[PDB]
Image (cartoon, rainbow, N blue to C red):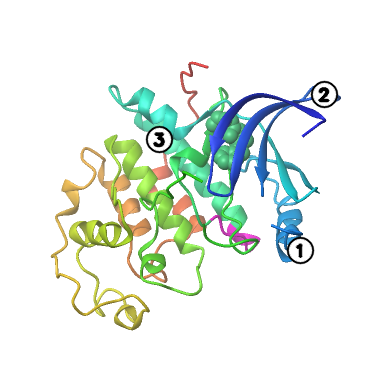
Amino acid sequence: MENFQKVEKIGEGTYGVVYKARNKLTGEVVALKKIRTEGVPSTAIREISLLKELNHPNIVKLLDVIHTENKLYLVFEFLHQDLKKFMDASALTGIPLPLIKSYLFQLLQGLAFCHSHRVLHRDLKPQNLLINTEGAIKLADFGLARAFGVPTHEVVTLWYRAPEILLGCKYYSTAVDIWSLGCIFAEMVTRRALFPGDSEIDQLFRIFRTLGTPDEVVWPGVTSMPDYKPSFPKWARQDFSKVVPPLDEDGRSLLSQMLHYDPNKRISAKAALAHPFFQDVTKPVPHLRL
Ligand SMILES: C=CCNc1nc(N)c(C(=O)c2ccncc2)s1
């Protein structure tokens, strides 16, 4: 904008570009997202202005929404690093379990809050989980699909997409976020993406190959879904101890519940917080190189 100075470009999206900026007047440093077009749909600006009220310590604060000259600016509190970068930097050593558990616990708290207020993220990924030096981790760049929908030179990653979305479900439930967070949990533990699909069908088949091709037994209604094909190959579920070694049984149990095929059987964020895995949760600080 004009009340700001683009320190640097910190991100790219199909929607818009993200900049680290400094408020010429208040001096506060923020992340600024710029978006495209002929009048900007209002049904969007309303679901957006509503997110300005969704305040929680584990949700990146949306400071302002500014619609001007066919441009939409979202001003957010700035964090210094995202989990994707932190994982790459911790890849040789691995994030210590206590920190993984603390991050998973905080993210479930952020989701429990969003979900209790009927708001879904829809596009959780390491790149939009932001961390600070205080040991906090926060949810950012909400999918605002209910605000806009589902999305140059920016291929959308499908690695964290819940199976019901890939199968063409018309209505997303809060379970899509739990699925995405389970995939992230597995990735933090193993230091490798759980289901790195490079196309929608490849994404779906990688999930099937690991968790077994779903059927009416484990997911009632699955065979009636829009993109379900009877011709899908039938893979047997793989031994789950092979999925996230060396994660302990409490962690494996919780992950397995976050990855249930049936959105109705999938654990909620609130129930996940009560899982035995968090009996010894603590809040360590990460070592950050900024
Ligand atoms: C991760 C380091 C840069 N600092 C950031 N800080 C914040 N708050 C960021 C975002 O809210 C964000 C917006 C749109 N897409 C992705 C992230 S990015």
For mark 2, what is the residue? 24
Query: Which of the four quarters of the rendered structure image does ligand 1 lie in?
Result: top right
Dominant secondary structure, magenta: loop
Q: Are marks 1 and 2 in contact (CB under 8 Å)?
A: no
Residue in the foreground of this view, choosing between 213 and 146: 146
Mark 3 / mark 2, whichever is N-terminal: 2
Q: Is residue 197 magenta?
A: no
- Badge 1 element: helix
Q: Position of residue 138 (x, y in %)?
A: 57, 39
- Place residue 78 in its image quadrant: top right
Residue 58 visible, this angle: no
- Place residue 169 in its image quadrant: bottom left
- Badge 2 element: loop
For mark 3, what is the residue? 100
Report the span colored magenta: 115-121
Give the distance between the C-alpha atoms of the residues marked 3 and 1, in whole angstroms. Answer: 39 Å
For mark 1, what is the residue? 42
